[PDB]
Length: 120
Image (tube, rainbow, N blue to C red; front, top):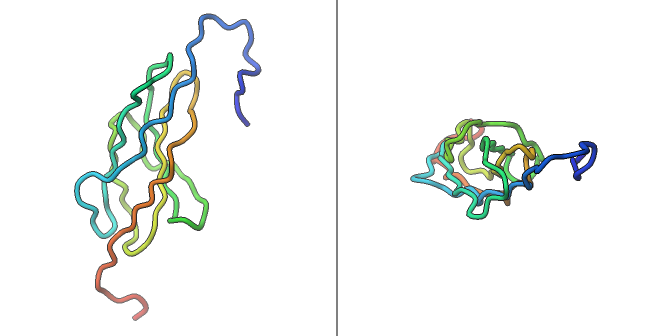
């Protein structure tokens, strides 16, 4: 479940839990099925120093499916393998000594539907 300040005992001047990163926004031009997203850093970071910025992507609205897509420091990753004329949910979060904290709102980005065949 959640740490809930449980388990670990006899702590020692331990830092506080980090904060949620700024919702991921679109950067540049959103192509058919390929767009980059960059999230601003925490304006009020707790008593912890960011360690890594992990992001997740899900199939539009319906179909709750979140799987790691990027990992590193750069506050910007290209979400490839997308689908045109469809929805997509994304969420960014920061990781620190105190594990990961609540995720950012869902970033709904609609891709442009190219004029092409569907069924054939």
